[PDB]
View 1 (tube, rainbow over the protein chains, first blue to last red):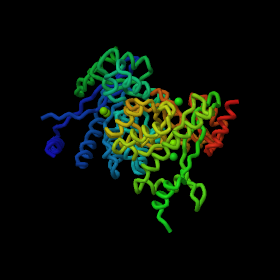
View 2 (tube, chains in turn cyan, orange):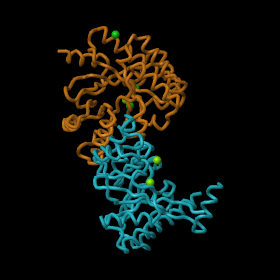
View 3 (tube, rainbow over the protein chains, first blue to last red):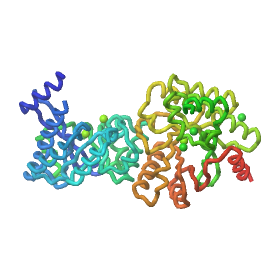
View 4 (cartoon, chains in turn cyan, blue):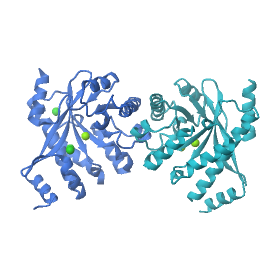
Length: 242
Length: 258
Ligand SMILES: [Cl-]
Ligand SMILES: [Cl-]
Ligand SMILES: [Cl-]
Ligand SMILES: [Mg+2]
Ligand SMILES: [Mg+2]
Ligand SMILES: [Mg+2]
């Protein structure tokens, strides 16, 4: 409760900032995405309020980079959405508000929803996901492999992408179990027309394993830790010049 | 009029339960390589009663453990009978449906050991089918039973697959040799693109994890070919054979031997 207290005060006082972790096209090395991650610089209502802020902040940041000629047309940014945000009407409203104020092209925004959303899959959740899809926003399943999936729902739901959990990526290719989980996820995604981001790439062996198996995308401290907006935009600049 | 519980207890003491067996076929050859044991109640008052009509009541009162143990023993005894008669080939196994309630107190380990000891059946000839949603109730006790059974050489498959929830990390870590695609999906392929996609997804999962697949509910030649062409190893369904009384099943084994 003391932790929620601190976050509330941080929100009230505007003491939060987004950092962004580059998401790279493994074959080219091109930064094509970035996961927005909340940092503090020193209750469902709190989740909702934080997400409203994150959504607007992230969409505004990308729109700003586009207008300054720093973000290429292929750059998208991703925001993490809690399963707890599907209660009521608020998520679709928050996304609509962020897009309206920023003027951002909706397919520039991607929402990362943890796998265990499938465990709370009600009619209201399915309807929310369809509503979000109808707006042109990209949807990804996050932490994939660590939660629970219905193979029927996975085959039906409008997710364009999956993110392989870091806990598996960090153990390949040495460990058979984690390695077969990763290669299975890649095969699933291929048949479902989903793109895959491998989260938590730490070593060059991991990068190379993943690339040589058609894993589209990667993110990890190997390439870049989460970066402040200005540091992230520097990477975009160097890439544009290259 | 007696309660269903009273009548079920009487069915056990009066030997009114029976097993039927549905052939499991290797798609590539058309060979019967297995059989799923399926309990019925030969109810003197009603005829051949299906488990949907009594198993829920068994579960309400915990009679399900005694009932499932009866099934396990009867199945092991039957396979041993066919083996001794020379009618069951060396590759033949039979599969028994297990209730998640059997894991309680690690009962299942003792129940399987008893069934094997009473029948003399080798563990490598017995397969167990546990519903996919066992993954939502995965405790150290369940994991202990599963590891014990794999250690014995008893093969383990996930039943009703696609109608429940799976953890990819559990599918990898747990000793499941196979899964069985639910008939509700297979029944509708390729005509219904949604069900067809579900089947394709499950096949990719199983192949990825080195698991064998039985597609249940195969009703048409087109479905048989769809699955076979996509490397699904085994099948079960009305196209090949409905569930059969023991003597009927054994006759199928006799025909195949020729
Ligand atoms: Cl049964
Ligand atoms: Cl039934
Ligand atoms: Cl023997
Ligand atoms: Mg994320
Ligand atoms: Mg995770
Ligand atoms: Mg079964």
